[PDB]
Image (tube, rainbow, N blue to C red):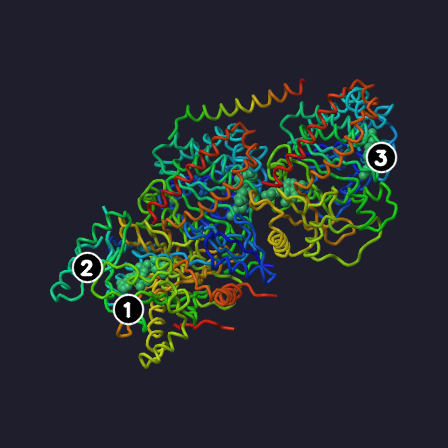
Amino acid sequence: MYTFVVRDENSSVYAEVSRLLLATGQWKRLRKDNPRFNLMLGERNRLPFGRLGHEPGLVQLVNYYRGADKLCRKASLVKLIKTSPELSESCTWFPESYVIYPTDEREVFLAAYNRRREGREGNVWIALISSEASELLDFIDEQGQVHVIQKYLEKPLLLEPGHRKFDIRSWVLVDHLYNIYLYREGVLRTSSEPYNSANFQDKTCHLTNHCIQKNYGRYEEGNEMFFEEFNQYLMDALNTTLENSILLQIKHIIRSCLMCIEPAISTKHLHYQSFQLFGFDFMVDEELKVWLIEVNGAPACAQKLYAELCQGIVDVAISSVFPLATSIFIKLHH
Amino acid sequence: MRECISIHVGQAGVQIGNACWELYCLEHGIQPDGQMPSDKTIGGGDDSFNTFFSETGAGKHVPRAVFVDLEPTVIDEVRTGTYRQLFHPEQLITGKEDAANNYARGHYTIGKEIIDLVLDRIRKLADQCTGLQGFLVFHSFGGGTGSGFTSLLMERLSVDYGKKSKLEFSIYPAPQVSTAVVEPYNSILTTHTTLEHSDCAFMVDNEAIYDICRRNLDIERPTYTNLNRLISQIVSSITASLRFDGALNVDLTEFQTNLVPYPRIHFPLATYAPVISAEKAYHEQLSVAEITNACFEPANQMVKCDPRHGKYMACCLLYRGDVVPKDVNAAIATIKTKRSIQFVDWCPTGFKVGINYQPPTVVPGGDLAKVQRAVCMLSNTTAIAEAWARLDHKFDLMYAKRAFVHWYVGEGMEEGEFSEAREDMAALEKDYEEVGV
Amino acid sequence: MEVIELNKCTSGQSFEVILKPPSDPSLEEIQKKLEAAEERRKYQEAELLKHLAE
Amino acid sequence: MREIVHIQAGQCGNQIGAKFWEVISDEHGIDPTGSYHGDSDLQLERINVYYNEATGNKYVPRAILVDLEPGTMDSVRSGPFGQIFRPDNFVFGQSGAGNNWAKGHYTEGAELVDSVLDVVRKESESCDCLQGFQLTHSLGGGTGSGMGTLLISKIREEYPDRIMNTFSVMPSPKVSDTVVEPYNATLSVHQLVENTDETYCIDNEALYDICFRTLKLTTPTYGDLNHLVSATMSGVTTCLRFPGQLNADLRKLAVNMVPFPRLHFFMPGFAPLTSRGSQQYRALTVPELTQQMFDSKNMMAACDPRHGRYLTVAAIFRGRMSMKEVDEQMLNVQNKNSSYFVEWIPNNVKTAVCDIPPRGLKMSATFIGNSTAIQELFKRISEQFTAMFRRKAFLHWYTGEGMDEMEFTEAESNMNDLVSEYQQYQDA
Ligand SMILES: Nc1nc2c(ncn2[C@@H]2O[C@H](COP(=O)(O)OP(=O)(O)OP(=O)(O)O)[C@@H](O)[C@H]2O)c(=O)[nH]1
Ligand SMILES: Nc1ncnc2c1ncn2[C@@H]1O[C@H](COP(=O)(O)OP(=O)(O)CP(=O)(O)O)[C@@H](O)[C@H]1O
Ligand SMILES: Nc1nc2c(ncn2[C@@H]2O[C@H](COP(=O)(O)OP(=O)(O)O)[C@@H](O)[C@H]2O)c(=O)[nH]1
Ligand SMILES: COc1ccc(/C=C/C(=O)c2ccc(OC)c3c2OC(C)(C)C=C3)cc1N
Ligand SMILES: [Ca+2]
Ligand SMILES: [Mg+2]
Ligand SMILES: [Mg+2]
């Protein structure tokens, strides 16, 4: 018998993980404040990492990597890149991004606005989306919190029929050994309303968020395209495959991100043990070049894919540490 | 030359004291009967070893130490032990009945009756000192005596010797080698009373020492002796600069300067390498690069915590054995590029290095093998606050129900002191937060 | 990178290597706390011997 | 903190008391003559805890023998180890207490109590550092019940800062002398709540059931019951009697076991359970001892520990065994059954291993547990009390000795208080 605790209210993913753990008949859920556990399915904020791996006679494992917030928070991820020599500004899979504090890098941001003005080429940035420099700075000081100003992709890849916009979500599981596992199924969060070309002010066709979109469910069920339908489309419309044109770059971006932070976050020689499920958000443009948007620490999975991925987490992240008395992932070797 | 007086309080203090003074004697070539053939100025002198040992006309070298326990059993083994002639009986003080795992009984009840005798016996050693610089206090966090009597003594020593420096060697409690269920209570109570009276404090988590003995020395179930011989090695490494010719950490004031910028945040993390089994037949001797790299592995620390998720304020590297500056600098250069060593913005990313060419001394027959080189890293990291969070949470669980409180109140202590001690601790946790993140 | 304050002797040598630059209660107060706790002990023992008298 | 003063009162008190001195003298290698004959220096290193060094190198149990009837104390004097006890320490009345708590506490026993206290005082003055006192007695009789609790009250007044330890034998209809036993027990519990530091709740129901169900004896005697009592008594005193890795102490037990001063009633437990004489040949493994000592079949108080929660546990393992295996098993119990231990007292189980085994058994284990399940014992007595007291039945035996109905209502209230107090932490 193994023992676990649940400490995350909202987590629909780890609600399903706990459900599958109890169902195996070898895992007993204890009360939240019981210290005598094998597994913690911890909270989003203020997780007590310092308390883990200190109970005698127990191997302890947690579903979060400490310090992985440096990849998942907007302002941190931008800093890590323009810092981590492993990446440096000399990046090609990332967009030109800047951090702005409300009453810092403003000397650097205005130098990029000037050189883009010189060639008169597309000078559009993101948080609302505007073209002018000083008409966006009033928005940052109004809201209160620190926000990132990122180069808006003015020419994105368009799905036909519809003349649309989309973003790809990949699910990545990093085990206790720091094996990077990419889930073979991803999802395309689509905009049903055709993408506006000159007008920047429009809302629904520019952003592709599942919550903010709710034209809903016009072409595919719930504005979500699975990997077989998108592979088939690329084969007919663009003569290429998903594996070659998009997926190779995705694998490179995932691998480069987690290899960078490995010395800082790895639980290789620790008293406690960590795994984590990540949500990488991508952007394919007209020339089939893949861009990174952000990483998710507590990611939400696609409704049809829950049963297989959550079984996969149990398979290689949990049962590898706690065996019971096959692979749905692609291992990204390093 | 400025002298240091060692005070050992409770069972843990006394027994760790035993191992330390045993080790100091082997380092300086002092025999059981207090004789030292290598010493040429018979009767006295102001050498670096004279900081810890005073001399008599007979040629005997006597530890500048006082052992105090409220119970006879432990110190009686010192009185009858292999180093019985080394101490004069006035240095060894014992009561009738112990503090029975109760802080309040050790601080208020049984403390009051013995406190004046102890301070008088301390003064008797201070008057043998031509220019005393301060004290090293050895105790447990979880004992009745260790928490209770120490905190009272630390209060009184700030009155009688306000100019002088005080240093703590504290045994943080672990369930693997626990003696009392109220060890979290005793620990929070003592820290609160001691915090303003302590200049620099070295925490030794019994958990970490227990695991090092299991992992690196191959002992299935480590005894108190197994832990104490390992702790004393770390203690010896820290105190070596006071007992030997050198230019780093020459006095106790320099420990504050080098390791303690903020006065409240005064708990530097010790890390030691290498710990090698003597019963191990084949061993390949580790290099300067290898032993320095081990200082940043959590498995080798005196307290289990992650310095990657925290900031440094000071870092000392203390080498014993075949070590040269060239080899050290090359190791630092390689490590900096591989590991997450983050300092606070208001501090230089630096290392103060001390080398002593004489390799570490081991107790014959003991579990520790002879090594060509060893290192002890002392780093004031904000990561040590993990040990505070752990202990505070354990305090919170019991105190929420007022469990065991009556034993403390029944000794004249007030319930308010508990929550005063706890809020001071919560203040300390947030002091580490401000500096750390 | 820079090696400063290098001191050598027979016993060993010590130095500093910098990689990067930066960016009490009285005696009377003790007795008053200790004796007030003896007052609360004596009060509790007296209240116990009063109860046993009854 | 070394010397313990032992007091045995009444028929049950002296019978379980004599058996205790018989068992522990063998363990320390002491003959009926008082001379040492054993083959280990470890037998004498803490003999000062319960023995006094006699004239010409002989040991004398530090004990005091008390009864209002001269019958039972003659049986002790003529018994196997009867000659070891100091002759002056035999303090007896004549007319007996006739199963009456009032006669024990207020009238007959009031006459004799001062004679006992002079013997207590003579023994206490010899003690270098007095730890406290241990009483063996039943709560169903008149002497051990009534006068025992009177002695306790008087000893507390003379020695306010010493420990009070009791081995209290709880009455059950299954092994019952008189109908008035629920009355005597309830009045005695009232006293023990107020005036003792630690109480080992030896329940006669549990001892009977162990003898009947587990040990397969169809009609158990008092001897069969007292075999289990003496085995437990040795087990719960082992750490005070032999040197260990912890400097074991009656105060340190109280401090560590009693989170709230009223809740100081412990469930004793023993593994393996054995009948008189007939020896078992297969020695129990460490996982077997650990599994049994926590099982309700092995408890000396007839309570189901699954019906409650453990506040604190203390375990003592006796024999030549792997200390790592002991730690592993003890942690396995706590980690497989973490709901049955309170989360608000961290690391609430302490374990010791002593190398010296008891007579017969190669390796044994003793349980001391402050479980909230003990309320079942007190509820049982309370239910039997109310059945009679709701009709004021049998009360004339008490009122004829000067007692009032008020005192019975107070005692009932205070026990019901203790039951609801244990109940409070079974939900917390
Ligand atoms: N490392 C080490 N720890 C010890 C030793 N002895 C006791 N301890 C630890 O110290 C704590 C208990 O403190 P003790 O020093 O035994 O107690 P004390 O100060 O004698 O106080 P009382 O006996 O309660 O008056 C526990 O957490 C033990 O693990 C020792 O020799 N070495
Ligand atoms: N630089 C850029 N160029 C083009 N489109 C962008 C962009 N930055 C953001 N977007 C679009 O805006 C949407 C919102 O992404 P963003 O990461 O800013 O918010 P978010 O964190 O709420 C999404 P998630 O919940 O998946 O993490 C994306 O679906 C993307 O299509
Ligand atoms: N276990 C056990 N219980 C006993 C023994 N003798 C009497 N009792 C119980 O004790 C109660 C009567 O107490 P007893 O000691 O005989 O009366 P007293 O001498 O007046 O205190 C009854 O409930 C009996 O079941 C004994 O030898 N062993
Ligand atoms: C809740 O955890 C504990 C429970 C009990 C103790 C007791 C420590 C002792 O000093 C002691 C004293 C007398 C004893 O005989 C009855 C024992 C006894 O303790 C042991 C384990 C050695 C066994 C029995 C401590 C803690 N932490
Ligand atoms: Ca000299
Ligand atoms: Mg002690
Ligand atoms: Mg009878």
Callout 1 amino acid: Trp
Q: Secondary structure at mark 3?
A: helix
Q: Is residue D228 visible?
A: yes
Residue B204, position as x, y percentages in the image? 46, 48
Residue position for label 1: A93
Q: Secondary structure at mark 1?
A: loop
Q: State the image quarter where residue D71 is shown.
A: top right
Chain identifier of the residue bearing label 2 in the image: A
Residue position for label 3: D76
The picture quadrant for ligand 2 comes to bottom left
Chain identifier of the residue bearing label 3 in the image: D
Are tags 2 and 3 found on a single chain?
Answer: no
Residue position for label 2: A131
Q: Is residue D82 visible?
A: no
Residue A88, position as x, y percentages in the image? 26, 65
Residue D327, position as x, y percentages in the image? 61, 53
Dot 1 crowding, Cα within 10 Å, few <14, some 14–19, many 20+: some
Q: State the image quarter where residue A261 is shown.
A: bottom left
Q: State the image quarter where residue C52 is shown.
A: top right
